Image (tube, coloured by chain):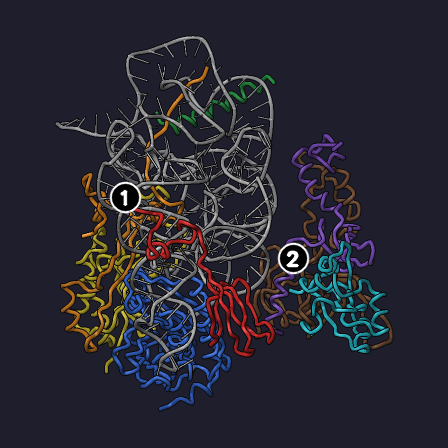
Chain colours: A green, B yellow, C purple, D cyan, E blue, F brown, G red, H orange
Amino acid sequence: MRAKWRKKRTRRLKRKRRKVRARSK
Amino acid sequence: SQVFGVARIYASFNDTFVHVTDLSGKETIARVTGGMKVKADRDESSPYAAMLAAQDVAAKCKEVGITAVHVKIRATGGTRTKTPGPGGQAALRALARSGLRIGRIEDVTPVPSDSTRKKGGRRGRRL
Amino acid sequence: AKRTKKVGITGKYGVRYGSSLRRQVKKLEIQQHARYDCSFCGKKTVKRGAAGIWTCSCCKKTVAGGAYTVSTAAAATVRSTIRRLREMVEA
Amino acid sequence: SINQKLALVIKSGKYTLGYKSTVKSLRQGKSKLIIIAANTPVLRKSELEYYAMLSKTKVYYFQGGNNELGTAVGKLFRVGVVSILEAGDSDILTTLA
Amino acid sequence: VVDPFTRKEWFDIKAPSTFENRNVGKTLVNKSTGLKSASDALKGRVVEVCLADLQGSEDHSFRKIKLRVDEVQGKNLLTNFHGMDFTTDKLRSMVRKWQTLIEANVTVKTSDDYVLRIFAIAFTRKQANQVKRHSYAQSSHIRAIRKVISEILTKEVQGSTLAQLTSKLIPEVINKEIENATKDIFPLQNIHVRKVKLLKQPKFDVGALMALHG
Amino acid sequence: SGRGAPLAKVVFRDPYKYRLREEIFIANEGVHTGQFIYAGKKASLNVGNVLPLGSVPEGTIVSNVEEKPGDRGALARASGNYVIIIGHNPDENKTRVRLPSGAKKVISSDARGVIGVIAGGGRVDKPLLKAGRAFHKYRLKRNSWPKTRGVAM
Amino acid sequence: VLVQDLLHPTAASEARKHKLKTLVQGPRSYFLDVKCPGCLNITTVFSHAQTAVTCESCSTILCTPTGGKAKLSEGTSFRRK
Amino acid sequence: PKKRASNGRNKKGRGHVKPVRCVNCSKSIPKDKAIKRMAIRNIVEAAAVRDLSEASVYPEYALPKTYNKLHYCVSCAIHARIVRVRSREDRKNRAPP
RNA sequence: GGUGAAAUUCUUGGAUUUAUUGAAGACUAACUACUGCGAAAGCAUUUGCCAAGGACGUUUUCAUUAAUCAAGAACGAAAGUUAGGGGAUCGAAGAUGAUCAGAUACCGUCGUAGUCUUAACCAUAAACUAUGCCGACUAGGGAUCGGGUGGUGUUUUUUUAAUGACCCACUCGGCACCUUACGAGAAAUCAAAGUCUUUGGGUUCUGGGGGGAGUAUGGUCGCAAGGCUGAAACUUAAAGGAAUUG
């Protein structure tokens, strides 16, 4: 797949992981 | 040394408008659109509609009192196209044939001195 | 030393009322308790005794000003408009 | 424009800064010229002008406040009016009036 | 079913004295019916028409002049200068690559009520025997010309109403001063007056209008 | 107290007797104690003066404008607010004006109104912050605070 | 090109070149002695202006400054000294 | 330790200039790229020139021209307008005809 | 209206349509170019004020003051965010009518955020000549922007004076270009990517097969969105760059 959309795919999952980790803290 | 008029040919893509008027402007006589004569409605800007209606204009125009007519020429302009439509030439020749004398002509398109965003999107119209 | 990092004058409210509100207030409280310069005596002696009223400490003139500043933006432009609009009638 | 003149004047001939001193100078006859600030008050202005018309001293109105009139004359304090007693190296008498 | 085209009463509008001939406008509006008399209805309207039609000289096809009505005298009325333009195509002919365009204006006053804007224009020619294709202006000389031209625009008006103005306009003797003043500053070419229009209209004033018969 | 716009105590000489009769406008922004205040028909268009609405141009900012001739203040009398005269209707001497809501109005040219904005603009820019401040604001107005919600009772 | 002498070139192919890119660097600025209109005595002046010079005794304008060489006003004779 | 990757190829311009939308299809485009043509034609066609001249009041008449500058988006230029595509050598040449 | 064609749509509770005015924002057309400035990002209407800067001129002065630069710092498109204003066109979302097997996509008709501006933030971009900066030296050729020099040159007034504008020759500093390759290069191409196996003029920064990954974690800046700094296990024989046919 394309790089521009890959970037977005990363980003969305990163700010999911931000909530997932910050549920504990 | 005879009576005059003015035509003002607004010929666009997908419609043609040529409505002769009095020398002042407000006193109109016969509107005649592109879609009046023919009833196909994809041929709104076609030659045969514009030549048909151009005689019809002169019919109602002779019925009051018009001999000569100036022929100012216009387009949609502004943001859009700013280039004359298909049926303008169809009109011009047709009205020049059907009875009337022909006065002076010039361009009167609404040409902007740059203005507003054009309709379509940045990446543009595509198919 | 330099006593606090960011609150400044709004640290009197302390922990409360929400950050965005505190900052929002601070934005004004600086201007409210600013010593402004007089238009007449030309010293840094103008304060306010109630919002709207702006006093000169020496000189002792009192100018009608804004809520939290002496010359609020809208006022500043109004005078200029009037200043300009007087030059069509007279000269 | 005018600052350039006063910079030269303030370090060659001689001058005076204040109000009382200016009045004194004006009384005696030494006053060649006065520079009144724009901000300085109307009563004081008119007063100075009245002396000026009697001593026949040429009157100049500065385009700037008292802070500015200090800035011009190379002084780190305000000065509502500056009266001149001797135009030394410069020639500020006939350049303006 | 109505037939409202023919019931309108016929009419004609004539030009002012300061041109050459009066016979121009032949129009219709409406009959003087119950409410809305056509005498006062048509006053606001104007006619844009070529100068060659009312000058008796076919060389001036460009410049279509605008004329507004005020008085009515038995369906054979007199009219007074409203505005002017050049023809759109003429400007586009004037506008070329490999040269510089210079446009300017000023809100000059006449002797009376009439206050207006007048838009001047100039271009830069391939002077005499240039080898280079363009001959561009300097660009301090563009603004320095704009100043001289502006001055000319100013001092040539504050004169006797539209009477002197229109007179100057018809053969454009304004151009000569613009030419010989600018000649030393920059070669130049064309030099016309694009537009003139009334920011401040007249107030009625029948004395100026009706004292212009043949 | 109970009006964020500060007041302006002005003193004229009565024409018809030797005395100083005092009036009290809502102070327009940029006035100072011992500024002169010119009033009436041929007053200057300087901030503080009270001219009839025919005498001003259009685009003009006034405040405290009367609804009709000689009612002594009516519109734009709040802290910060102001009207904008946006054209004459010189026949049957009215003038068309821009009220601080947005909505328009047609009123006599003989209705006076005072030049400029009103002081204390940007009063409501600050948050009231703590209930106490609100209480303090309201106890100099009336007893419409605090307000219990109907859905509770 | 290829083989030539740069020590002794020609005045033709050197006076054309820039002041800095000659063999020995030298200015293109002679000194001129102007005889003014008023007085009979001379005024020794540098060919390039910088400032607007007036006469020695009877103070009137001699030569105005430009982008390069001095603009000597009116009919006034001069020398190369 | 440390290890990764890539990048690519080239062409020339100037700095930045504002765009002018496509006269046909409303795509945005600068003026170094541009692709422009001068539409310079009479109002009348070759067929219309006689029919008019015959019906013309005024001797000599006029017959002006509709002038306008048309800007394309490269995509649309190849769709119709004179641009097409040239060889390895011919794409260096700048002469029109 | 609107397209490839249809529809949505609005229509004598006069629609689209010409002429006379007004209101609001909008953007500086055409001229506008292998044209101009800025450190870049980026900047085109007039006029004024405020400082600033290049080149040029210079028998002016200063006298190695300098070249680049980890840290640290100003600016930094567009889109975003914060609270006001402004809120016309165009228009993420959205609603829609078509299209099609499906269409929440392309085509249409509207339309909230935005586009504009005030004060704050934000720091990324194919921020592109994906070509560090300073210095020197090497091939020709014209054309052009900005000074400068000279010529009994031409042109323009008041024949003539002065400038300007031209023409010619020349020289400095640029935006660049045309022709060769003298050289360089894997080629494409390059007057610099040259003067480098006959390998060293000064200096900063970055890369060491592809992925995993510009991810994880930890710091740090940010209101947030994100930004800077930045691995590992594990996996794999090619990824790739130019050209060559087909």
> Residue at 34% across / 47% down in the picture?
G6
What amino acid is labelled 1 in the image?
Val
Q: Residues within 10 Å of mark 1 (few under 14, many from 20)?
A: few
Mark 2–mark 1 CB contact (< 8 Å): no
Find residue C22 and report its image quarter: top right
Return the x and y of residue F94 as percentages of the image width and height: 60, 70
Relative to I39, residue F61 above or below: below
> Residue at 65% across / 57% down in the picture?
C76
Residue E205 in view, yes or no: yes
Relative horizontal placement of residue E50, taking residue E207 as reference (left or right): left
Residue reaching furthest to the bottom: E214
What amino acid is labelled 2 in the image?
Ala
Find residue C10 and report its image quarter: top right
Find residue I213 and report its image quarter: top left
Image quarter in which the C terminus of chain E is found: bottom left
Return the x and y of residue C58 as percentages of the image width and height: 83, 55
Residue that carries the numbered disc 2 in the rendered image:
C76
Q: Decide which of B97, D16 is in the foreground and name it.
A: D16
How many numbered circles does the render carry?
A: 2
- Say which of marks 2 and 1 sits in front: 1
Q: Decide which of E90, F114 is in the foreground and name it.
A: E90
Residue that carries the numbered disc 1 in the rendered image:
G3
Mark 1 falls within which chain? Answer: G
> Residue at 38% across / 63% down in the picture?
E137
Relative horizontal placement of residue E97, taking residue G31 as reference (left or right): left
Relative to I153, residue B33 above or below: above
Image quarter in which the N terminus of chain E is found: bottom left
Mark 1 secondary-structure assignment = loop
Return the x and y of residue E118 as percentages of the image width and height: 43, 72
